[PDB]
Image: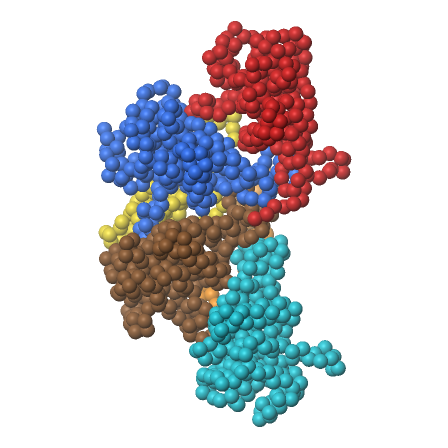
Chain colours: A blue, B yellow, C brown, D red, E orange, F cyan
Amino acid sequence: SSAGFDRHITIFSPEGRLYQVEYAFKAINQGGLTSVAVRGKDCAVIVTQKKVPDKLLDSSTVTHLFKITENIGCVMTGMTADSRSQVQRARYEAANWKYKYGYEIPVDMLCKRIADISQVYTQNAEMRPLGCCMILIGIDEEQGPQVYKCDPAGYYCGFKATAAGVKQTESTSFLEKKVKKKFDWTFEQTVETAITCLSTVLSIDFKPSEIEVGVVTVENPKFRILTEAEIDAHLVALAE
Amino acid sequence: LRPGRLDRKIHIDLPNEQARLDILKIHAGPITKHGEIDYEAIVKLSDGFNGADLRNVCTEAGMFAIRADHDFVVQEDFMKAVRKVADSKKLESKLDYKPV
Amino acid sequence: TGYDLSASTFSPDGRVFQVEYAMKAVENSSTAIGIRCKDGVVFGVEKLVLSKLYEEGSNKRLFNVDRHVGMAVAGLLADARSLADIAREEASNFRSNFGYNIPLKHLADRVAMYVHAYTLYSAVRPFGCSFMLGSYSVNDGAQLYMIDPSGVSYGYWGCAIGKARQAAKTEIEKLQMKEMTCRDIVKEVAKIIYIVHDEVKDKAFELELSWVGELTNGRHEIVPKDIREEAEKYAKESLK
Amino acid sequence: ERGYSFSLTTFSPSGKLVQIEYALAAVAGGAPSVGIKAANGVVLATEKKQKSILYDERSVHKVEPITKHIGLVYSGMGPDYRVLVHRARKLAQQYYLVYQEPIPTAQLVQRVASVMQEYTQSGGVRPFGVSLLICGWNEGRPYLFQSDPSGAYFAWKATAMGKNYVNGKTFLEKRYNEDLELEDAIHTAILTLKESFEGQMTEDNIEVGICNEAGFRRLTPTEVKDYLAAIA
Amino acid sequence: GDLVGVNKDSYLILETLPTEYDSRVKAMEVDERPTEQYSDIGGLDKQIQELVEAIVLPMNHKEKFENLGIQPP
Amino acid sequence: NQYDNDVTVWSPQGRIHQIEYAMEAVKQGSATVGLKSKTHAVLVALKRAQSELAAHQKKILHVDNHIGISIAGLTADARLLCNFMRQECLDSRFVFDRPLPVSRLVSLIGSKTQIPTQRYGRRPYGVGLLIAGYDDMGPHIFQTCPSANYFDCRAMSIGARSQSARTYLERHMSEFMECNLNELVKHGLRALRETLPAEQDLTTKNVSIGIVGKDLEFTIYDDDDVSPFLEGLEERPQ
């Protein structure tokens, strides 16, 4: 199943596999983190946890939610040093869309340009292919809300509900039973069904100081990050 | 591992912070202490621990009490006991394992 | 083995050892602590007197990047002052292009992306330094950041890097840095680095302190002699 | 930075390029896909199963157009495909800016396969892990070509790529003749993709694109449901 | 599980033999007392203490752990 | 040891072995001792030869009128940093029309030699520069090392068998900040007779002295003008 330096660099195994990429997928799992994204009928919600183990650390500088453009937000998993470098590219690629083409970049075209860059790392046998993932949300005209994931292999797809991190398979098994019964989704139900995803997988039943929620909706297309006070409003209504 | 011979596959995992609170209170029974024990802060640093090393924390907190002849256990000796156990398992292997 | 020679290869469980091996080189440098007060940041470095032949004021582990930004380093000293040169040069390009003094959330962002850039290729090694950045502005207050050799930065109310890291930050959270001004902090900065480093390992050592805030009128400079003599007067009262 | 500037693909002592032989193993483990030309147009049909019900199937596409009259499918790994699509999109433009004419389908495969050969000799790169099927109707007569990661190409009447491709080629050999219409070739392309799919072949588990003399186009899932109905 | 001494012919047990130890375990036992003293070990006085007090204190002050009440390490 | 091949590779203990092997190169060259008073900076070297008819290899070099250096290691990398040293002094004199300060010169060397200690296929510079000079702040003694780590000091000694010279400098450095040029030199000359075998010491053809002084340009003394300094030393006690 191995011959040559196929364990070390990005070349083909005798089985057709290539191991340096599928080693990098489980470099995401060393963060100890899990993020959930849910698309609604007229909105898009990202929820993720934050774990602050110290009192000496400033809790306002640990946000994994990042604002890419004025109308595009994202969440980052994996290791922190590679994830913040990939946000810096996505800020740069969106500004060049506006300068060259004169209008706001669609969120699927931005995920294509990130996945094309990540392809080149697993295409040359020199670079290390950036072991961190990527989840974007955004409102598109004549498409509504839409959610995309980009992995460090260069693959991407549009989702309807999304999990990434340590507890990915347990969260998606919860969500696929939720979506196929096909209830209609208001704004607050998508907030409710996203918090109760990682509250039943992780079994926490938390207070509002450990999670962070970004949202976009077609009445205010600005990507906005919720205050902990209004996080608490959805949380005490979740406990009926 | 065929389902004819072994039927169910019960999985036991690393304890949660509720369980780490629960396991700590069982091993902290017969400890001559003073009632200022914030049990959360011990659980706050207790990450990825076992059920076994929480008995060690209760064991090693008395090992700070065994010096300077304090027959009582101050609350400060617990946060000394956590940080010494916390880096002694830096040299572990940490592979979970899965039945296949 | 063979999976840990270059920084371009992951391990078969998905982590890079050349960064972890360079993180181990930091805990052989001694100790650098820095906490921020209510209205400023105070650094502190205990300096090992290796032999009598060196001069008092040699080989300072406490740099001066910009007019208001300070740096305290810990690691392989040749890589310390090499990172200090690009950070000193990065702030010069900000003032020349944008007109004003660089903020810390941008300065530590540009440096950490420069440190991260050497954790990807086989042609270069990771740095063997971790360091702290602290400053004061009249429009933003006091800031305090810290950068590991992987390239991760966060905000802190107080941090510690060196040999005894946990044994230093255990006593930092005994303080109350939210309300103290940067005068009584100077006595408390020195005291927590006398209780560390038993006299069996080192014979004699040197105190070196730093200081920034509006009491210093925004400029970064060293403490005066008389103030650090008060802290060295406040040295030998920890024997009770 | 810089590169490596040495070929990591060498000759074996038995005289075989081993990395190209391994790249064909990754092609054979891809999704199955068939392609059939019959006397007025070419049918390209593939097999696209999402792993779960959470995926949006109307987001990505296997069947891609290159120009007004050239489509292109694959059977291999995903991210390598989108690279040489964007390469082949550009190569059709530099032919058009010189000659003011849509590119012949033969001359596109001359230049796409020249990229893949150039990429298996140069320094510090692993070869591609995809094989292609290219259709098009230039000057009345249709065309159907297949490339490979080595850089060669062929001129097929009907062929299959992906898993169980050796069973599809026996199935097409007992099915295809010289005289079929386009709607007959659609019906036998679904009949050969049913050899290897799961139990449910719905309107969104497959993806079909055709050429005419009216040009290349890609079928919507409405009439794909009508072709999937009254099948097998 | 016991092992006893039996007559040959009658198969009638006579005595009760004490122990069952392999001879290699008897070679594992010291009887020589290799004399070394703590002054001969320089530069380990942190490790010397926490090795002794984690072993010798449960062998000479058993009640001292039991006064507080913990299991010893 | 597979961690022992290239400068890029970290050890699992975190100590790059190629830097530590260049420290072995500076320990091969002969000893030299530098020290300073309040107003002077004197460095004394000890030459070697191959046969008795070949000449002795010089070590003290002239960088500028107020800066001189002393080398230890392989001589080819010494001239590589020496021609960098001379170039950085006279262009600052070309631009600003002033002597370039010593403490600002050495930081250019520390950034110069750190670059090949991080790339791939690039050796470090095996060299042993002791630097003596004048700022506007009086004398300065600086030493470097192939780990690109320069040290501010008041008396140091590097080369083969130099630990014996350092023990002499520690128990007499309380006297150094008072004396004139005469017994400042022969304080340092008593350090070089410490680092020798017990039969040959100072035979006026293997020792060199360089002084920069508060009204004195940097001057090298070689094998005839050494003899006024070298007389006035007592015999070796045995």
Tell me the quarter of the picture where residue D42 sits: top right
**C23 and D228: which is toward the camera:** D228
For image coordinates 65% across by 83% down, the residue present is F206
Q: Is residue A100 left or right of residue A7?
A: left
> Residue C31, position in %: x, y?
41, 62
Q: Residue at x 61, y 19 (%)?
A: D135
Instruction: Please give the count of numbered marks on the rendered protein.
Output: 0
Quadrant assignment, res C231? bottom left
- Give residue F133's position: percent from left, percent from top: 51, 77
- The image shows residue B84 at horizontal and vertical percentages of 39, 54
Q: Residue furthest right?
A: D14
* Residue occupying the point 54% across, 36% down: A119
C211, above or below A157, in the image = below
Q: Nearer the viewer, residue D75 or D197?
A: D75
**Would residue A220 appear left or right of D210 to someone viewing this image?**
left
Q: Residue at x 46, y 22 (%)?
A: D57
When the figure is inspected, residue D176 is found, relative to residue C110, above or below; the finding is above
- Quarter of the image for residue A223 reads top left
Can see residue C107?
A: no
Residue F56 can be seen in this image = yes
Q: Out of F183 and D58, give the one closest to the viewer.
A: D58
Q: Is residue A157 above or below residue E13?
A: above
Along the viewing direction, whichever of D96 and A136 lies nearer the viewer: D96
